[PDB]
Amino acid sequence: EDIEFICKTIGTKPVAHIDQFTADMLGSAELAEEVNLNGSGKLLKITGCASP
Amino acid sequence: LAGEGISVNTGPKGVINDWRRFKQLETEQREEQCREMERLIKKLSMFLQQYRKQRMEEMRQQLHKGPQFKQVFEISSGEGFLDMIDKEQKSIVIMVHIYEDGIPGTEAMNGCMICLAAEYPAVKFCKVKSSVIGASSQFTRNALPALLIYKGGELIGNFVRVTDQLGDDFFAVDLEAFLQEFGLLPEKEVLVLTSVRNSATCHSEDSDLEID
Amino acid sequence: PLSVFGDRSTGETIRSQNVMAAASIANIVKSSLGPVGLDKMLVDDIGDVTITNDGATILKLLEVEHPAAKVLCELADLQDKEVGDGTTSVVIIAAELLKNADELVKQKIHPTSVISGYRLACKEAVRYINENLIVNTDELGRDCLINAAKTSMSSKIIGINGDFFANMVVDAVLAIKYTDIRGQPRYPVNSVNILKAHGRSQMESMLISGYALNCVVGSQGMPKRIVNAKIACLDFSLQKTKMKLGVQVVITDPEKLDQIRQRESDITKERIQKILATGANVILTTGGIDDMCLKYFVEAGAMAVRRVLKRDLKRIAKASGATILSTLANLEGEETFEAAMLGQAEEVVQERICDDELILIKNTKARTSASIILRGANDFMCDEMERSLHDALCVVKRVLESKSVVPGGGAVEAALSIYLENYATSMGSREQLAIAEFARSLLVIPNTLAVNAAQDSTDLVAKLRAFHNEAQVNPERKNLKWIGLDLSNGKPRDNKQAGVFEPTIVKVKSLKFATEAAITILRIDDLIKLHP
Ligand SMILES: Nc1ncnc2c1ncn2[C@@H]1O[C@H](COP(=O)(O)OP(=O)(O)O)[C@@H](O)[C@H]1O
Ligand SMILES: [Mg+2]
């Protein structure tokens, strides 16, 4: 259910077979890091996207 | 006497509170009672073979553990029975014993359950009084020793009158073999004794790194 | 009229009920605050015994019904998770704040005004703490860390032996120090393996300059001591290779069954030979090892350890330089195991600890690790030592990360109370009452400390308040901000020169959390309890 949201946010196009997995279907991003919430859990953020 | 067609209409919707007050208590009542219908009524109505290894089985079953040997859990009330039975998962196997004081056979198999729980940590051995369970008084005469086994809401063991099938002096080996040959007792595993304990917790993943 | 199947409480009744629940939770642990606090102990229904002093542990063990009481319990849990210390003071402060706020509300003061006053008071208290009551640890040196650890371990089972336990804690924390990007030193606590074992006294607790495993060698054949250890860390089992679910063996020519059966274990034999041919001495795996592979390791004079915990193996691999291997597959599609992925250590032994054995990986190279073995009188005592040790480690981590500390013994609370009492007159018309009540509720900490020591709480708190008032009103006697409470003699004392410190983050986070919890509870003025 999150595929549409992820694709809209980043710009990646889903790949269902390795034959069509090409560079044009990748969403560029300036930073993709996993941050620590002061010991309350690990949160993963992708901040900064080409063509947001 | 006429007007048989009544159509009580507004009445029941104006008295929902009290009717539901009765209904919740009745729901608790027959949920508890039906949790023991599936056992009641119908049960009561219805030279290697010389066990050379039995003695040495008892011999290394004597070494229970280091920190004491605990005891068998006791259920206080039927509501307690229900709220300890609906919890946990399917993988947990539960054996429950109904008993009364003074009658023959209870102490021996109670000690058997104690040592089994000592050397079968996975199982959840527990015992409950016949008065507490509120079973039919026919059980209260002629169905006290009942090695009852539950597994996640459904019966997996159907054993009553265990005195006839085991005796009165039967030890841990006898009941353990009788339970395992019905495919109930899980396979044992090689378990060792650590110093005391190691795992305080595992919640934070800040462990190590060597960034320049 | 409502016709709702449940019970409804409205107005002052529900507010009084919430205050009662919060006060009950506070009074549960109010007797376990400060060095004169005494530990509690809990017995479960089955019969398990837990002797403890930590407020968070006590509140976790208890089963609680009232929602506000659950709120305070979860507040203590949050304070434990995000800070590690002060889990009792936060609960006490939150309950006192709720009680005083409800007392204000009962006087027809609107709850919104009280909430705004509490918010402003918390903000100004944090600002004043950060501006006046912080002491930099740069000029104090290692003595600051030692004093912080000693203060944290006071009121615990290891309080009197603090002179040695603080040294052990500081050494353990400094051992696991690492720097990351942005050039910020980091101290990953919980990477220090805490091992418990009853036996000798507390003073025999050992700090390991390496790592400690609660595991033994799989077979008695292998040696129990290797000098120049070449640790190989694997994340897969060493057993007979059974084919996957999608592969089925069907035999039509009987002459090949023996070859199939032989290869079924020759695969594992070849894998172990590849692993051993590189010179490895110690092999650690998270999976199981059966008898054939154990014999293979025995014949080569190596060590094989099975069922190693994943976190322990990760820590060992990171410390010794080894790399975790799920499979022995390289980028060329074959089976290889190079020597570049072998870990190293100066000694690996299997010490005997009170009729039990554990593996010690001593003096790992390429990274320094640490572990602590706690020796106590029995299991309960060892558990309490472990909890207190974790509290001390968290306190030292907070001190080393943020280099600001504040005096202990209620000095911060008294200073904040005086400052807020003075400052409330300059803000609003009805918010000033809320700020004054915030200042008064901040005084519950020194009052509880004095009470637990059977000292005259009223006179001690009056003297503390007089000292802090004179400090704030006289610009030439600012040195009195450090006047705390000396519970041994029941007199005020300069805590800064007495080595009674604690991280500023503890006070700031506790204040913020307690204020927000009190605000959350204060908003409720009606309860609907639907019948199950
Ligand atoms: N040696 C000491 N002298 C005076 N006060 C102390 C001393 N050690 C600790 N305290 C104070 O006792 C208070 C209670 O701390 P404690 O209850 O042990 O922490 P927690 O609240 O995490 O359980 C702390 O606020 C601290 O300022
Ligand atoms: Mg503390």
Image (cartoon, coloured by chain):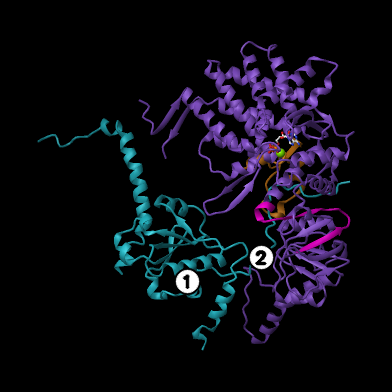
Q: Where, quadrant-wise, is the C terminus of chain C in this rendering?
A: top left
Mark 1 element type: helix
The three-letter amino acid code for the residue at tag 1 is Leu
Specify start and end residues of the magenta stretch as a single range: C358-382
Quadrant of the image occupied by residue C464? top right
Q: Is residue C416 magenta?
A: no
- Left/right of residue B45 with respect to residue B109 in the rendered view: left
The answer to which of C356 and C451 lies nearer the viewer is: C451
Q: Does C386 sit above or below residue B193?
A: above
The answer to which of C332 and B137 lies nearer the viewer is: B137
Tag of residue B193: 2
Quadrant of the image occupied by residue C30? top right
Which chain does orange denote in the image?
A: A
- Percent of width and height locating residue C449: 68, 32
Question: Which tint was used for chain C?
Answer: purple
Which chain does cyan denote in the image?
A: B
- Left/right of residue B127 with respect to residue C370 in the rendered view: left
Q: Which residue is drawn at 49% across and 29% down?
A: C17
Work out whether residue C290 can be spotted: yes
Mark 2 element type: loop
The residue that disc 1 covers is: B179
Q: Does C452 sit above or below residue C301?
A: above
Question: Mark 1 near mark 2, Cβ–Cβ under 8 Å?
Answer: no
